[PDB]
Image (cartoon, rainbow, N blue to C red):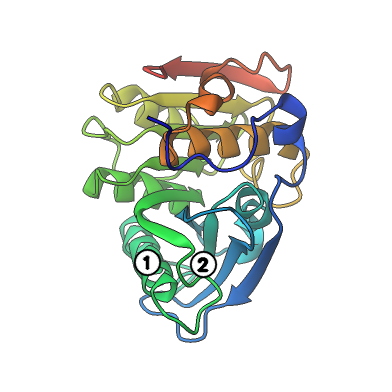
Amino acid sequence: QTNPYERGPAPTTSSLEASRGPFSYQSFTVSRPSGYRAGTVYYPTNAGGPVGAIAIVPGFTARQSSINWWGPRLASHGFVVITIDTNSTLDQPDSRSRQQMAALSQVATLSRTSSSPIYNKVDTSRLGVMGWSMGGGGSLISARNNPSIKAAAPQAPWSASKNFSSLTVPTLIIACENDTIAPVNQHADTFYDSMSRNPREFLEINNGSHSCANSGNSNQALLGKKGVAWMKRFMDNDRRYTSFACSNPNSYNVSDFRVAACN
């Protein structure tokens, strides 16, 4: 069979490194956020069918601005994205996971609400999780707790829980070589090395500080290509993105690349 989740034309290096995919996007603020503080929903106006939904959580003391470049980037390729603010900026990773799932729950209900810009735009069975630092650990925790999640792509993850051996959710860990907040060999390395049952990839930005994948970063061409490709391959089962998702980028801006069980 045709894969009914395929959206957009065949990807290219340049179409993926571009700021924007083939779809127009708009956004709205969530009026009455349920179980988190605030949310901006990015969506394609014209994806040619329902698309999956991704919730993205900031790090400790941070807000939507740290992680919201992902909103337009992913929405323009055919995803509905919610970037959230947490109940408290001091929330820890387990709390962030709960709020991440709550945000996905509300994206889903809004997609079933006739009032909403995203009415009928979402396949609420196809969800992804992303986030920075403690929001990244929350994404791992979400994936651990809920194996039906299709994909995880946290960045510079921080988590006091170290054991993700149970993960079957395809996970791309974005890491920052010189991270002094969520040091790679105490966080990202440990998380990755615990995994064995899931498609997975480790993409570490050369000399990256803790904020190496945040809004305004100097590696959007590479990071955006990889994040979109991962979400396409695993959220849409879209085999046109296997090579993009699974390949070594062979970039000098990558200090360490690892991959396993990726086709």
Could you tell me how far apart the alpha carbons at marks 1 and 2 are, in whole angstroms? 8 Å
Tell me which corner region of the image, top left, top right, bottom left or bottom right, holds residue 109. bottom left
- Return the x and y of residue 168 as percentages of the image width and height: 27, 32
Type of amino acid at the residue the image marks with label 1 = Gln
Nearest to the observer: residue 188 or residue 102: 102
The residue singled out by tag 1 in the image is 99
Asked whether 196 or 184 is in front, the reply is 196
Measured as percent of width and height from the top left, residue 186 is found at 42, 32
Please indicate, yes or no, whether residue 183 appears anywhere in the rendered image.
no
Locate the N terminus and report the quarter of the image it occupies: top left
Q: Residue at x 34, y 62 (%)?
A: 101
223 relative position to 188: left or right: right
Residue wearing tag 2: 84
Residues under numbered marks 1 and 2 in contact, where contact means CB atoms less than 8 Å apart: yes
Classify residue 111 by image quadrant.
bottom left
Question: Residue 250 versus residue 115: which sits nearer the camera?
Answer: 115
Q: Secondary structure at mark 1?
A: helix
Image position of 40 with respect to 172: above or below: below
Give whichever of discs 1 and 2 has the lower sequence position. 2
Please say whether residue 184 is visible from this viewpoint. yes
Q: Amino acid at mark 2?
A: Ile
Residue drawn at (57%, 33%) of the image: 229
Q: Is residue 175 above or below residue 133?
A: above
Number of the label disc, if any, that sits on residue 189? none
In the rendered view, would you say 198 is above or below 92? above
> Going by the image, does 209 lie left or right of 161?
right
